[PDB]
Image (tube, rainbow, N blue to C red):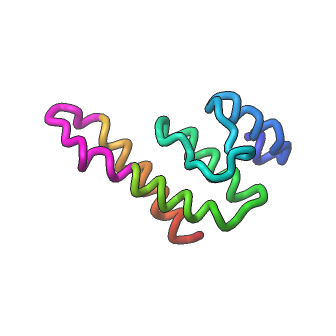
Amino acid sequence: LCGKSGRLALAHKTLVLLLGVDPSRQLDHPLPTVHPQVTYAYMKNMWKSARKIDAFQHMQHFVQTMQQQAQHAIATEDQQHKQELHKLMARCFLKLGEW
């Protein structure tokens, strides 16, 4: 909602506060692959705000890390955890294509 209203600086501050790490100073290292939702939000925000290129590579990497999870961790019981993964990674694939 803050991003929609345009006061994007507050949104960026809130994201770095919740995430705990600020890649805007550490440009090279990848995003913290844990907590896919907050990183997805930060990625959408950084696409929108200024940078329109390195976002693509971050998406590539984040996808190849997310689909890496259940295929390399074939849980025999956790079936209610991978469905949200499927839906989220479908979202990110579509964003990838249209970008």
Q: Residue at x 69, y 35 (%)?
A: 16
Q: Residue at x 56, y 71 (%)?
A: 98
Using residue 3 as the reference point, say whether residue 93 is left or right of it.
Answer: left
Please tell me which residue lies in front, 12 or 61: 61
Q: Residue at x 44, y 49 (%)?
A: 88
58 within the magenta span: no
Q: Position of residue 93 (x, y in %)?
A: 45, 62
- Specify the farthest residue to the bottom: 98
Disc tally is 0
Quarter-of-image position of residue 49: bottom right
Quarter-of-image position of residue 76: top left
In the rendered image of this protein, does residue 85 appear above or below residue 94? above
Using residue 31 as the reference point, say whether residue 64 is left or right of it.
Answer: left
Q: Position of residue 73 (x, y in %)?
A: 24, 41
Q: Residue at x 64, y 63 (%)?
A: 54
Span colored in magenta: 66-80
Look at the image and tell me in which quarter the C terminus lies: bottom right
In the rendered image of this protein, does residue 80 appear above or below residue 92? above
In the rendered image of this protein, does residue 53 appear above or below residue 14? below
Using residue 23 as the reference point, say whether residue 34 is left or right of it.
Answer: left
Q: Position of residue 75 (x, y in %)?
A: 19, 37
Q: Position of residue 25 (x, y in %)?
A: 74, 44
Look at the image and tell me in which quarter the N terminus lies: top right
77 within the magenta span: yes
